Length: 120
Image (cartoon, rainbow, N blue to C red):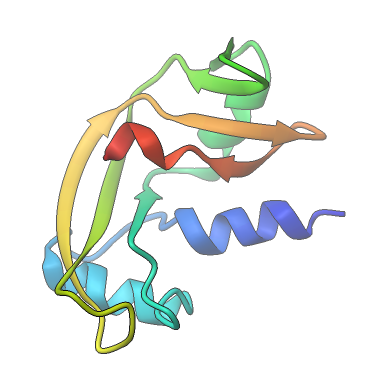
């Protein structure tokens, strides 16, 4: 019911990250259980949760493509991209810190999906 929103938070939300370098990515990807198999790309959104939720309303969002929403405001983000040939741990990640608007899918006014294509 709210399980998708809570899984969005686990996969894509980190309120106040510690130094957004490769070691941040390798650590947080483990902590969030995204390392079996190694997820190929994943982006974390920083700042407060309320700004992300607001994308689902007209406050901080517009409709986008087929049933996505795109934010009006820009977010501090960090993209972890897997390096090395192997799908399996240890999972080495290159971090790319970014600042831009983001694309989500909303369900019941909650974000339940992050569109990763924009960070590739």
